[PDB]
Structure formats: structure tokens, C-alpha cells
Length: 86
Length: 86
Image 1: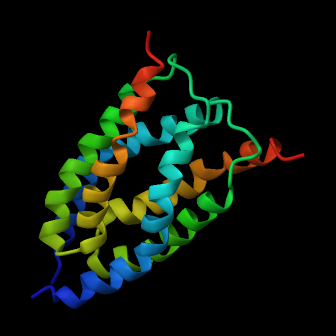
Image 2: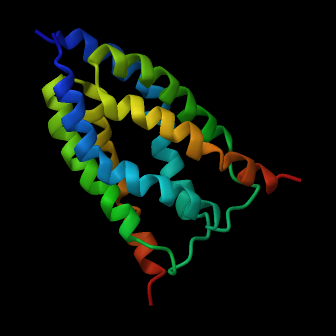
């Protein structure tokens, strides 16, 4: 019945990107982005993440669940990007 | 036995981000990134994606499998980023 042990193994491997992804998100902010960038692209990505949470639960996978939580917190860099506007 | 129908549903939803993510990748290139950016972060992300393919197959999920294939092709934007070097 979809053993939880599988989720743990996936997280362990995904940890490399997840751990590296978090700091990488901040670096993107210093990438000197312009306001003329379509923020709509980022908004869509967030929508997929929200849905991925449901799918992740159905599979009992941790990487998708943990990624969604981590992304939400790290995503906070949205305010920084929005600063470029106006 | 992990019905394939589940993978199809996940892809349909993930299609929003997957479809939007592809064009978003190109836009990142025009983000005026600097060579002083740690490319190592991107390298690690790729490693996780390669492993995710195996995990994705184990779950029979299409979003992870399709994402890996799409990312590999779209990732090609690596050469553009490498151009900043030197």
C-alpha cells in the first residue's frame, strides 16, 4: 500500500536539489531581473505546485510534498521581484 | 498496480507549469545574468532531475518523466549561461 519508506528514499535523493534549490532561489533575486519580466510565468508555476501537493499525497511521495512547503517559504522572494514593478 | 491513468491525470494538471515553464526558461536567459553566478547550483539541480526519472518510473508518474525530458531539451539554455564565462 504505497510504503512510506519509498517517500523517504526519494527525499534523500531529492535532498541534493532541494537543499541546493533553496539558496539558488535567493541568488536568482540578485540576477538583476527587470520589471519587464512576465511575472505571470511564475504565477502559473505556483499553481502547478499547489496541485502537485494533491498528486504527491496520492503517491505518498515526500519530495513533492516537501518541495511544495519549501517552495512556498523560499518563494517569498516574490516580493523582491515585485519591487522591480513601478 | 499503479494505474497509468493516474500519470495521465497528473500530466494534464502539471501541463500548466510544464507548458509555461518551457518558455519561462528562455526568458531567464534574457534576465541579464552574470558570470559570477554559481553554475554549480544548476548542475546539482540537473543531478536531482536524473534521479527523479528513476523515482518517477517507480511511481509510473508522467509529470516527472516528461519534466525530465523537457528540462533536458530546454536546459540547453546552459550554453547561453556559460557564454557569460570569460
